[PDB]
Structure formats: structure tokens, C-alpha cells
Length: 131
RNA sequence: GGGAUUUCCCCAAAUGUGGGAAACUCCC
Image (cartoon, rainbow, N blue to C red; front, side, top):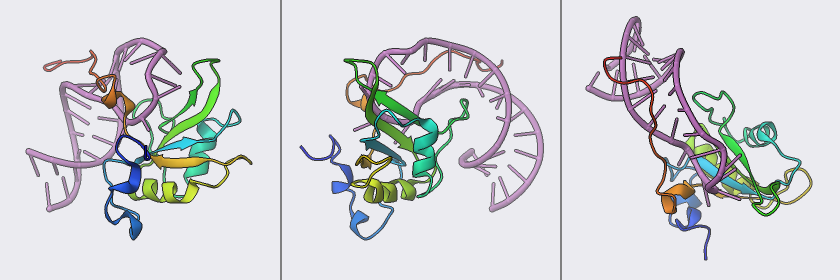
């Protein structure tokens, strides 16, 4: 039960009187988007709370719209990373329960799903020392 | 010693913040 396996902003501490109480959680998860949404829509929809974090090589904001594995189209889930941690907590308390394009949506903290089953992320080849 | 900037390399489905390496300048 609860928000997630980390419990959402439930154990965050002073998050009831402050928009901080986080630092390693500048990311938020979103639900209810629908198929009408895209990277430019989410980032342009969330940026009003604070700046969306940019990827270090793709140049786009750090977003991805998730899809149904049973049909291969938008599930209505997405994940938006904020460039600032206090903007993520505010965007959760704010966007959760309102609409996005006419349909209702939800928002919560986000934490890498891979660290809970896929063993988390992994390194890859490239340049090396003395190169 | 630390922080910021720049550059280079790699798979994609899995669903929620990728890693490694090099250089210069600036700030503490």
C-alpha cells in the first residue's frame, strides 16, 4: 500500500510545512497524461513550478512517456526531473489531483525502479585514463 | 582538495534521477 516502496512524501519529515525535505529526489512521477502528451508538453507543463532538468547529451529535458506493454501506446504515465529539488516537492503537492489536458492527473516523488529489481543502472565503455 | 563550464564513448524498452574518461577557465 501507500505511495511507493519508499512511501512517497509520507516519511519525508517537515514536508508538511516546507517545500524542501528532499535533495536526492528532484524527480517526480506522473499519471493520467494520456496519449495527447509528449516531452515538450510535460516539460512545458511542469516548468511553471521550477526549471526542468536537462540531459547531459540529448539536450532535451529529462522526461519519458511510459507505455502499455500490452498494446505499445501511451499508458498515461511519465517521469519529469526537476533541475531543483524544492520544485519537485511543490510540483507533487500542486499537480496531484488537477488536470493536464482536460483529464485528471496524479504526481508523486520518483525513485529509480531499476534499483528495486533490475539491479539499478550500470557503466559502459568509452575513453579511458591516459587517453 | 571541492564546486561550475566544455568535450568524447555505449544498449533500450522499462516502465521513476545512466555511467566512465580528458582538457581549459573561473570561484572557494
